[PDB]
Length: 56
Image (cartoon, rainbow, N blue to C red; front, side):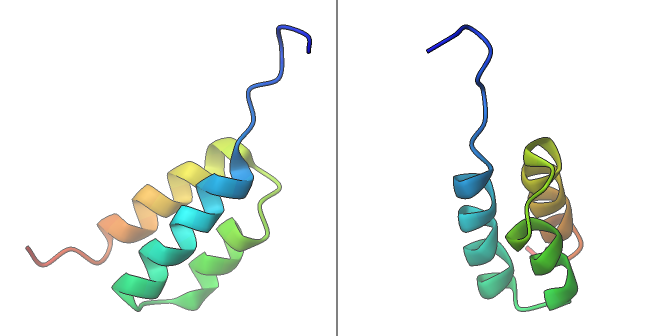
C-alpha cells in the first residue's frame, strides 16, 4: 500500500538485540534499539553500538 512505507525497525532492533546480546555490552544501547522510535537509528545504533565492541 502506498509508495511511501519503508519501515523495518521491528527487525532492525530484533537483529540488533542479537547484536548486543552476542556482543554483551552496554545494554543501554539495547534500549535505544529495543525502544525503536527511530527506524533509521535502530539500524544505525545497532551497527554502531556493535562497532564499539569489535576485537576481531
